[PDB]
Image: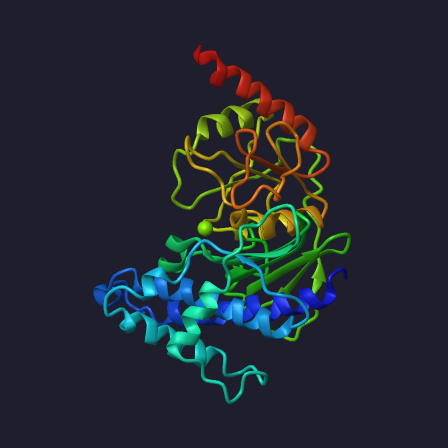
Amino acid sequence: MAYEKELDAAKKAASLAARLCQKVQKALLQSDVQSKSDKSPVTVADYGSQAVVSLVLEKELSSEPFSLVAEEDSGDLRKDGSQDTLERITKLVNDTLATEESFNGSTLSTDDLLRAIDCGTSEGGPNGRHWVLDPIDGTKGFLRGDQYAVALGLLEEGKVVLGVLACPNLPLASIAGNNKNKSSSDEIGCLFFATIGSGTYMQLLDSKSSPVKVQVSSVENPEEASFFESFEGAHSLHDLSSSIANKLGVKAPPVRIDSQAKYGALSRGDGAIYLRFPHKGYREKIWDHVAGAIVVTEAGGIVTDAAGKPLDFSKGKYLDLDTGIIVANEKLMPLLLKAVRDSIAEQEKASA
Ligand SMILES: [Mg+2]
């Protein structure tokens, strides 16, 4: 694979972040109440995921200065007697970063933990090499035990060259194909990774099982195409997705995932089409799409905006794009593009 050394570091880092997150989610009292605590689990998982990712990549890739594009800093872990959360993350990170055989006698302190979060303060851009991390995508899914993911990408001169997706709750089999109705399968927890010109692979998380190459759906007719939707999201400019699907005449049931693991499922061929249209004023962040984009691309998928333009990750943290994001295979994308821009020119522009 291209960027083989970076790919190994990123798969190790993302997998360890998934262990830290699973250790929190399984510790959610195992009851629906969760001790009635605050967003403490979500915050310690986010800060903890970002911490272990930063600490692994920095140790594994000692050949280059570390540059990470992340949403959060350490400003919250300093005001108030927040050591209740600061020290619980430090104990949480050290415990997870104990099966490493590289840190060993290290046991990072509370000050070392917040330095790991503040050392990842990059702004992307068209120059240099930057890691792009979402420590937990699908915060609501993480709480309800649903689908969440750790997204880790790499930019090289403003272009995405590597994506890694860790989906601890995603099963290995097709979630869209509920027709299986099999047993518990017990094979749950996927790892998607791809680098430029090298293909997309799927592996069992924390398992020495061989990775398998994955491809997108070979669906030819829009009627049997399947759409990805949100587990809770109702509106979100559905009127576009509806009229687009109406002109396409889609009759297959939708697939409902509530995290960035939507990309991993589409790249293995569970669904055929994904359409995201952000609300007015909301600017899409690069850590929400960079890792999933190349995972889909390197599996044969087409990831463009509304105008058919490729997504450009060189402009910083935000992604200026036409309307939303359009994902499909080579055969469905041309018709899908016409269905979108018509629905954009129709019901949308018909307001005037
Ligand atoms: Mg996010």
